[PDB]
Length: 48
Length: 144
Image (cartoon, rainbow over all chains, first blue to last red; front, side, top):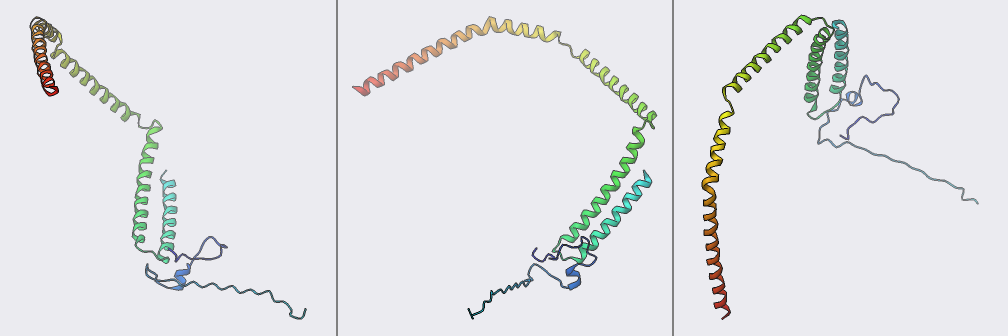
């Protein structure tokens, strides 16, 4: 259920699916990898 | 109707083929067979609906009035025969006898059972009096 194709909603019709293009066979015991990384720093000049 | 139904059936077949193509390309646990069965049953239901719809459309427009009139005549004759049979049944089993039977029964009851009712009342009165005497004697002995 968590292996749904996540994509930007631009086109309604998809001739080829994400899983169909990725050619992976997924079952109920396949852990799907997810990693998100967001890095932010507000750099200031030390020379006041 | 045949042309319209053929066009609609072809469109539905194209839509079902596209949906099945989408389904196969996507992973599923065991529901692909269920979806195929649903599509097949829906196609069969569509065919049955088309076949019944063409017949009912050809029938409503006053195009097969002869069959309707003949069936109505047959049904009316059937109802007439049933009514005649019921009239014969009612004529067979009359009701004048049961009035005399119940008259005799109530005469017998009023003439005989009323003294029996009084005798039952007197016997129950004696039994209750004896029970009360026994109970009060027991209570007096217990208090003593």
